[PDB]
Image (cartoon, rainbow, N blue to C red):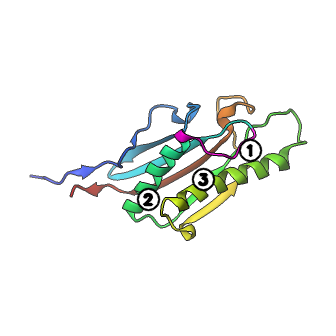
Amino acid sequence: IDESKYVLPAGIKQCEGNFNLTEDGVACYTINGDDVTVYLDTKFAYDKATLNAKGKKAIASFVNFIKDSNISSVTVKGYASQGQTGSEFDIYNQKLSEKRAQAVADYMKQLGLDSEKIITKGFGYNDTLGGIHKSDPRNQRVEASVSAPLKEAN
């Protein structure tokens, strides 16, 4: 006798298997029961902390979900690839990754999200993606995930 209809995050599609092994910026969702979780994987060109159009489209939809879910805070994590076999550039890439997270967060603020709701972390070329080489450009990225109950349709 149930009639309630729940609605999916706007402009975001369900995550495919290994959704982070895309070399494109993406935002996707998974459902676990009645709670939805949205992921953001924004990619960057080599040595760049600038956003591209794909990244910006993804972020905008990510933010639209945060503002609609009345979500409290989002942690924005930046990463880098390890381009060279030693540790000469570990601090360099740590800073790079921080700059990437800061880029993502700056754009979120342009979109009408408040700076207090945003926490940024850089990781350098640690936590590189599983299954690929550490120097793969897909490691050059910012990640974030938020969760919220599924909204009833209205």
Left or right: 8 with respect to 116?
left
Q: What secondary structure predominates along the stretch shown in magenta? A: loop
Q: What residue range appears in magenta?
A: 47-54
Amino acid type shown at disc 1: Asn
Earlier-in-chain disc, 2 versus 1: 2
Q: Could you say where residue 52 lies in the image, as x and y percent from the top left? A: 59, 41
What is the number of the mark on residue 104? 3
Q: Nearer the viewer, residue 45 or 16?
A: 45
Q: In this view, does 57 lie above or below 118?
A: above
The reply to whether dot 3 and dot 2 touch (C-beta < 8 Å) is no
Seen as rendered, the residue at the extreme bottom is 116
Vertical comparison of 68 with 22: above or below: below
**Pair 2/1: label in front:** 2
Above or below, comparing residue 120 to residue 84 in the picture: below
* Residue position marked by numbered label 1 in the rendering: 126
| Amino acid beneath label 3 | Val
Query: Which numbered circle lies on residue 66?
Result: 2
Q: Residue 25 location in percent, x, y? A: 54, 38
Q: Provide residue 3's location: percent of width, then percent of height.
A: 13, 52
- Quadrant of res 44: top right
Residue 70 x, y percent position in the rendering: 40, 65
Task: Give the Cα separation between the discs numbered 2 and 1.
Answer: 27 Å
If you read the primary sequence from the N terminus, does the residue marked by circle 3 or circle 1 appear first? 3
